[PDB]
Every structure is written in structure tokens, then in C-alpha cells.
Image (cartoon, helix red, strand yellow):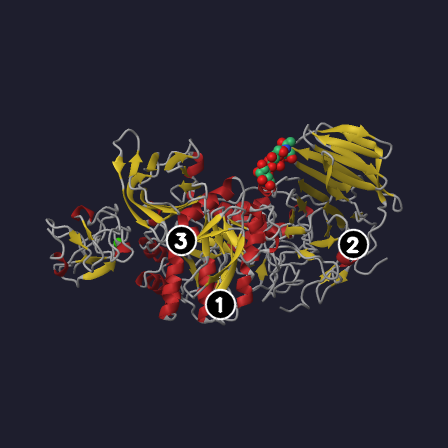
Amino acid sequence: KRPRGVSLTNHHFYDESKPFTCLDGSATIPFDQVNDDYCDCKDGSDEPGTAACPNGSFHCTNTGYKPLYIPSNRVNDGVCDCCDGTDEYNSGVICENTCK
Amino acid sequence: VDRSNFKTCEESSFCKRQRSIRPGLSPYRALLDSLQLGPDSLTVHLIHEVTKVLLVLELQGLQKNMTRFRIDELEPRRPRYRVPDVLVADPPIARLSVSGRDENSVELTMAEGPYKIILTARPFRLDLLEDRSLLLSVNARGLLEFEHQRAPRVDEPGAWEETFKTHSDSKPYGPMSVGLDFSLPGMEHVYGIPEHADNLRLKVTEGGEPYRLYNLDVFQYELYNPMALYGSVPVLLAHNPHRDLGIFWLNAAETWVDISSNTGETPQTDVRWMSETGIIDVFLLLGPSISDVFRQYASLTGTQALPPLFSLGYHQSRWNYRDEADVLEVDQGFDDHNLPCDVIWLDIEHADGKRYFTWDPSRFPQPRTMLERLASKRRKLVAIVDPHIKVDSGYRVHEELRNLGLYVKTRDGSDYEGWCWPGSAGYPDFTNPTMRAWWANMFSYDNYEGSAPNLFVWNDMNEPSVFNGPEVTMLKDAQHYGGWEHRDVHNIYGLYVHMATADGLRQRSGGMERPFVLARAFFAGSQRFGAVWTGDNTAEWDHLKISIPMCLSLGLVGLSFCGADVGGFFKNPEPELLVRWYQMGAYQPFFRAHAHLDTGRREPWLLPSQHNDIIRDALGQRYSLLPFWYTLLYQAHREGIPVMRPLWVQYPQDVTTFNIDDQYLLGDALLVHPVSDSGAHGVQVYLPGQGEVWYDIQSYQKHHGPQTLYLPVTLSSIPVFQRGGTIVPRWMRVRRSSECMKDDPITLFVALSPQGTAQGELFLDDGHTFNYQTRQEFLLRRFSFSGNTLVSSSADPEGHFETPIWIERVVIIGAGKPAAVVLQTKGSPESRLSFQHDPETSVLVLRKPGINVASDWSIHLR
Ligand SMILES: *[C@@H]1O[C@H](CO)[C@@H](O[C@@H]2O[C@H](CO)[C@@H](O[C@@H]3O[C@H](CO)[C@@H](O)[C@H](O[C@H]4O[C@H](CO)[C@@H](O)[C@H](O)[C@@H]4O)[C@@H]3O)[C@H](O)[C@H]2NC(C)=O)[C@H](O)[C@H]1NC(C)=O
Ligand SMILES: [Ca+2]
């Protein structure tokens, strides 16, 4: 049940029960603020899965392809950056599982 | 530049003849017995007391503080040229009535307003008045010159068959030059007649050559000279702290404008126009304000056509790309370095041996699957389609442009075949309406092969630029459509190429999609077809300083979509100059980087790391400000006020802003002073306005005008200020292009006036369609801040647009700690909004309003 845009390595810093921390340290935020489409955190940590941060990244786990951290501005941009297009989910553009 | 390649006033036969006449009693005198006041116009006959050939003067009032008068000849002999397709419509008429009659003068009130025209009879001298105050006098110095159709003779040299350097000009009609002078009392500052590489405020041409308005392909033009550049708009705006007028000299021929001023009592500026042929057609724009003469002129020629949104972004151009592969790698290099690029631009080499409307099967083997992967990454492509058509049996364009006679024809009657880069190139008659209809039909998706909806067209060298021609243009004795010589229809040719290409790009979609076209040569009324850029400029610091005046002067005459080549075109720049040119270019309306063969590759990502992130920040600023650009281009589209405007436009009474051409205003909100010096440690920014606060857009530090502040600068700093009392929208989520940015959350930067007020507008549309007009699918919102309330209303109730854009953040600059911030909406509960107040910069960031831009709302700083 990891938050959108987070790797398994990145999945223990995010806890549903606890308030989310900036993951680098500026201030803490309520978890409802993680992936809320607003840049609450200076690091850009609060929004791994949304394009709300000018400094964040989307981890794309690909089965059969190298996991890649695309820039956050490439999430929901209508272009399928990742091999498994998890980068597009609300943009109206659907991708294919090209992980071959 | 090679100055021994273009005509000075002494080498132009008519210019040295008109200029020879000197101020004195005018031989042209009005006969107030043929004075005939019709329902629309007043007709009088002027007589030349020596020549005894009488001309006809037609005075006409217009419904917008405006007066059009035309001087032609009573018995024409050969009809003279009257410029078509420049006026967007026939101007409405405000009738004239005799307020009084004299044995020597006639005074005529316009409609019922404060304007009266006093017409004297010995000598002829028009005197426009506002109540009892003189505004401008026509033929006040006695320089009205109208060379009639002489009897066939081929005296003075050059008045007939002439040779410039090696090119013959056999004038079959002899001297037909016209001329007229206007004295503006009280005006010392005149602006306009654009495409001259000089300052914004025109200089007095008393001991030098006058300003030439001639569409020429000037190779490596210098600066601060009155030489005619690629375009020509014969509009001259005069400025005073009290009254501002304008003179629109409608003539599509070669024109020289002589600026004069008295030493000395009340100040006065005398402006003399000399045209090679045609009639004397003058529109007089009687203000009384800057915003008024812009609206009047926009009612004459038209408003700046609203561009598509992607054209407001960044365009990248090399001196063509070697194949489809180079385009693919430049797109991938913009994607990999996370730089925002919208359009990739192809030069002449993309054509099949300089043959347009087609692609080489080996250079670009799969043209329409190159645009497919340019549209998958959501970017556009711009080709080159120039007027000259190569000569081939296999060229379908040439085989149809010659079969159907639509080429310009030389003096004998055969087709013009000037040797341009496309082999022997035939130049088509773009004056011909039936040829512009053929031109427009060939941009269709069936005619233009390898064409996609993201493929747009840039018409370079539409002056026309004839390589083996007089100067660099077509011979003046070339016969155009309707029997007109090229001498009559020169300055209108570029406008005709632009119009035909714009209607070609318009009608391929069916009229739905907006057309983006870029032209080098243009005339009055060319704002209605697309963008214009300041030709090919060298990559020096002086050509970057002069970028602003040539776009400020272009914006004054309606062509508010101006820009210069980022990084120059000649003499490849240093990395610092390339950095500073990407910072200025991000705040000009047109933002394109172009290169040459002699220069290397000037892509942003083969620069030093410090010089690449600064440019990346500069592109991010432009894309963030794109909503502001789209709103500003809409204001120029409706009321005609320029996007890039000088400081005296918004502050007419400031006599300090009159000679300012290093700073400009992006509307009423942003004041821009881009840095153009080698290693500049500081800029000197004049912040105008009595009782005005300007906030540094980066540091949020307020300054009280009017003052001259020293702003220390680094390589990373673009000196942009926001005026206190404005609201600037922004897209703070910069993407690869402006195609998903158009549906991204909006943030509003609210700068507070010293009275705690602010006001701004936001224009939204699909950004690529003529749907804001036919179905009114646009959205114009007014954001106001008064007391402690930020309200959002609709500034145009008929604009109903359904957009996914919401307001994600509100930035109030100069506010205080609220201790409570509420959001009220359409009966929904008043949801309290979180906020962060930085006290050092005094900036209040209201977090996630989360409200659609379409809906009305009110944020209360309780
Ligand atoms: C067509 O022309 C008419 C007539 O010229 C023109 O209407 C005029 O508009 C001007 C500008 O609005 C008016 O001038 C104003 O007069 C009032 C009353 O005397 C003054 O208070 C105004 O002063 C303002 O300007 C100051 C400048 O420093 C500012 O500090 C402050 O704003 C002042 O309040 C100003 O002088 C003029 O009275 C009218 N005249 C008539 C007869 O209506 C009209 O706008 C033009 N329309 C078009 C279509 O171009
Ligand atoms: Ca994507």
C-alpha cells in the first residue's frame, strides 16, 4: 500500500498512521497532504506521485525493465515516459505494458 | 552592411527632388468655389499657381476622433495607386459642418465634437483644432508636392529612365512622387515607422538621410541608421504630457520620412513624408491619449491576431537539420535536459533543393512520421515556404504558377525569373487575389505532402528578396496584377505573402485551428496574420540592446507579437551573451533561437553547467508567465494596446520615461529591464509613477516611485518588477511544452497598492482553436483585491469555458498576517484555507484554494 511514486526503498519513510516528514527535514505535514497535488514540502518529498513539485520525482517500477526516476513534471503530461506507464493515470492518455 | 548597395535620398531620384523643395509659400492654394460638402466628405480643388494643374483634396471626419484626407489629381491621366487590404473595414464617418466661412478660410466642425478643421485658401493649409487649441497643421511650411503625370518624354536627371548600380529602371510614367508636411505644435517626441535599427524616439533628419520605409533584405545591417530594414509601417505617433496624436501615411510605395523640429518659443515637430507614387492618403488620429490612438489605429488596420498558445512558448531553430534524425535528437535533447521546448524550426535545406511545399525523399524520407513522434511528445514543427519558386519541369508549383499566369512580370511582359537560392526563381504576384487563393489552397493536407496539424509555416524573404535585383529587391518597373508597377506595390507585397500564408494555414484545418505564421517583411495591418521578427541580426551586445527598441517601436503600430533572434544570426555569441539573450528573449512576445551556417550549434544543453541552468530557469520563467502572455496577447487582440509597451504609454505625464528604451512594460503589471552588458554588476532601473510601489519579482522587495534604483545583478538575475496593484497569473508547474501546461493549476501573484488594492485579468481558451470567437468558448476572469478581500468575477459574461484549471496557490505581496483566511463560493460552506506568511518579505501564501477558475469565489483575509 505504498504511496504513488515511491520505491520499495522509499516506502518505509511514508507511513499512513504517522504524519509525514519532509524526508530531508524542513517540517512535518499531515499524511492527507502527501500526494495532495500541492507542494507542501520544500524538498518535494510530499509529492512523489504528482506533478505538484518542481523538484520531486516519480519512481517507475518496471517488471523486466530498469526502475527509473522520471522528473515530476513528466507525471500526467500526456506522454508515456515510463515503460510501464504508471506516470499517466489521470491525464486521459493510456499507455501499454512495453516491458519486453 | 554594404552601404553601396541601397539608395540614399540623393540616389533615389524622387527623394532628392522632393527634398530639394524648401520651406516657403506653398504654390498649392485652395479654391473655395469648388468646395463641395457632400454627406460623407468635403471635396475641394487645390491649384498650383505656376503649373496650373489642379488636384482634388477630400477631407473626411471619422467616428473615433479621426480625420482621413486624400489628395489625388482632378484629371488623373493614369489612375494612381490606392492601397487595398490594409484597412480592416471602411472607417465610419463623422460628418463635417461649416462652423464659419471667410473670404480666405473655412472652419468645419467634425460631427458635434470639440474638433474643428480650419481650411485656408491662400496658401492651402489645413488646421485641425480641438475647440481653440491647435493640434497639427497640414502644409504649414509649404512642402505639399504632387508631381503630375508628365507627357511621355523618355529637365532633371533621374526623373525618367535611371540606373542605380547595374539595374535599369525605365520609368514609363516619369515623376509621380507625392509629398506632404505636418507641423505638430508642442510635440518634441515622435515614435513609430518601425524596422529601423535605431532608438525608439525618432531623431531629427535635418543633416542626414531621412527614414526610409522600403522592404529590403539588408544583409548584416548595422544599428542607429535610418536605413530601411525588412519591414515598413508608415505610422508616426507624437507624444506630449497632455495630447497625443498620430499620422498614418497610407502608401505602399517607397517612402522617406523627414523629421524636423524648431530650436525656441513653443516646441514643434515637423514631419515630412515623400512617397514615390500613389495618392496622398493620411489618417490623423487625434487622441487625446496613448490608449486612444492605439484603439483608433486598430479600428483602421486591425488588431494583433491572437496567437495559438504554443507560439507563446520557446521555438528552437538551427540552420536547418541534416535529416529527420537531427530533429529527433534535438527533441530528445530538450526532453532529456528537462528544457521546455514547443516548436522545432526547419530552414531552407529541408526543402528539396530549396523547393518548398515538399520534402526530399532522402533528406527527410518519412516526413509525416517525423511529426507523429513530434506530436507524441507534443511539440510542433515549422518549415520554410518562401515566395520564390524554383524552375523545374518536375516542380508542380512552378508548372502551375506559370500555366496559370500568376508570376510577377517584367517591363516587357515576360515572367520575372530573378536568380534566388532556388535556382532560377520565379517570383509570384502576391498582389493578385487569385494567386493568394492558389497559395492558400496549397497548404492543405493533400497539396502539402508530409504535412500534419502540428506543421506550421514561416515565410522568410517575402520582401521580395531578389538576388539579382536592384538593391536586393525586385525591379520597380515589374508589372503586377491590375496593371500596377512593382514601384506602387512594394511595401504591400510582404503583407500579401503573410496574408496568403495565414489563410493557407487557416483553411487546412477548416478555419478551426488558429494559424501561426512568421514574416520578415510586412506593412500596416500585418498584425492580423501572425508574428514578425527583426530580421537577421548579428550576435553582439549592441544588437541585444537594440532588441527592445525595435520591438517597442513595432508594438506601437499594432505588431505587438515582436521578437528578435535569440543568440543572434551572425558572429556567434559568447556564452555570457547567449545567456543574457535567453533572459531578454523570455520577456519579448516572440521567443525563438536561430543560427547560421557560419555559427556552430547553439543548443542550450551544450553550454557550461552554470550557463545551462540559468537558461533553464529563464525558459521556466517564460513558461510560468505564459498565462500572463496569453492574457496580454488577448488585450492586444481586442483593444490593440501592445503587449510590449514603453514606459510613457502607461505614464504619459512622466517626462523622464520619454527617452527610455532599455526598460519596457509587459502590460500594466511587469516592468522589465533585461541586462545587456559584458559582466554587468548592476542595472539602473527607473521605477515610475507618483505613489507607486514596485515589488522585485524574485526578492519581493518594494520600492517607491518615481525613482532610479541601482539593482545589482548576477548572471542568474532577470530584473523584472511587478507593479503594486496588479495580479499576475502563472503556471508554476513547468512541463516539457505548453500542451499539458494549458490544463495545469493557476497561481495568482497579488501585488498590493499602497491603498491595499490590486487588479488583474486572466484569459483562458483551448489555446489552438478559433472557438473563443465562433462559440465563445473562452474565459476572461477579473481578480480584484480591496480591503482584505480577493474576489474573482467574470470580465466578459459571454465567455463560458469549461476548464480543469484550478487555483492552487495565492501569493499576496505586501500583505500582513491575517490570523484567519476564508474562502467563500456558490453556497458551499466557507472552507478555511491554510496560509504561510513570510514576514521578512511580507508575502502571504494562501495554500490550495482548490477552486476552478471558471467559478466565482472570494478569499477573505479575516
Ligand atoms: C475623443 O475625444 C474626446 C474629446 O477630446 C475625449 O473625451 C475627453 O476625455 C479626456 C480624458 O478622459 C477628458 O479629459 C479629462 O477632463 C477631466 C475634467 O476636466 C479631468 O478631470 C481629467 O483629468 C484627469 O487626468 C489627469 C492627468 O494628469 C489625471 O491626474 C486624472 O485622471 C485626472 O482626473 C481629464 O483632463 C476630456 O474632458 C474629455 N472631453 C470630452 C469633451 O468628453 C474622448 O475620450 C475621445 N474618445 C475617443 C473615442 O478617442
Ligand atoms: Ca508522462
Secondary structure found at label 1 = loop
Indicate the amino acid at tag 1: Ala
Closer mark to the observer between disc 1 and disc 3:
3
Residue wearing tag 2: B18
* Image quadrant containing the C terminus of chain B: top left
Q: Give B118 or B5, whichever is nearer the viewer.
A: B118
Q: Give B716 or B453, whichever is nearer the viewer.
A: B716
Secondary structure found at label 3 = loop
Residue wearing tag 1: B680
Judge from the rendering whether residue A77 lies leftward or rightward of residue B93; answer left or right. left
Q: Is residue B315 above or below residue B246?
A: below
Q: What label does residue B254 carry, if any? A: none
Indicate the amino acid at tag 3: Tyr
Q: Is residue B235 above or below residue B98?
A: below
* Mark 2: C-beta under 8 Å from nearest atom of ligand 1: no
**Residue B342 visible in the displayed image:** no
Indicate the amino acid at tag 2: Gln
Residue wearing tag 3: B700
Task: Kindly indicate whether the residue at mark 3 contacts the one at mark 2 (C-beta within 8 angstroms).
Answer: no
**Residue B289 visible in the displayed image:** yes
Closer mark to the observer between disc 2 and disc 1:
1
Judge from the rendering whether residue B735 lies leftward or rightward of residue B35; answer left or right. left
N-terminal label among 2 and 3: 2
N-terminal label among 2 and 1: 2
Between the C-alphas of marks 2 and 1, the distance is 47 Å
Q: Give A62 or B809, whichever is nearer the viewer.
A: B809
